[PDB]
Image (tube, rainbow over all chains, first blue to last red; front, side, top):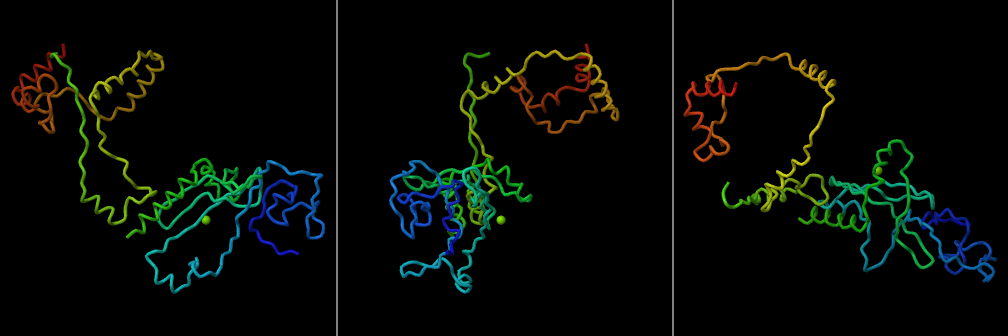
Length: 176
Length: 133
Ligand SMILES: [Mg+2]
């Protein structure tokens, strides 16, 4: 025990597990409360009221099967019938640094159309209140051919502009 | 000169709708792309002329290091020793487009064609000789 997945891998650098309440799962709780698969309330150690744990969103593998929902992967025949709608896509990311380590943050976004957007490194930091979409500090990958990204760590943009730009680009590319 | 200052304005450009429709039809001007519209016909309001003539206030008296200037002038001159110059008579000048404006007050009575066409070569050479003194 146990097979796990990089999905939601709490990549924070902090060392202590979670208090039962305000722990998302069972694996995330610390070892004190853990007594044979169960948690026990120890009023000795209390709950932290401020903590920032950058969470990872790496391998999300969807193959769900519902009726009223259209599957998000298509075969090689249906994708052929529906050309005129094909569009390339590729992403170049960065790495997390000073508050947490272990995952990737998107940084550049290309398309088959010549456009290249570039975002600011943000991540899904969780908090004692709730989850939170906030800025994170990062650094480029150490691969030498990735040195042509060092300037890009000081361009924007806030994601609320980037996604609007994407919507408008796709719109005026595929509307006809 | 006269009793009321004139205010000059600058009109906006003109639009060629057919070409724009063509270019968007063939898939240009996409959002976020690199090529785009950046060059327009900017309009100006009333006190535009004087507000641009005022830009001379960046010209200030300047005293130059006389010795290094007296040396660099020699070197610059040496950059310039492959040509040949000297005065020429009136009957050897070459004027392209004799149909431009002739400055102030002359522009009240025609373009440069008039004055370049109403003064014989003697008058032109006499004018040169005059300004030489
Ligand atoms: Mg790539």
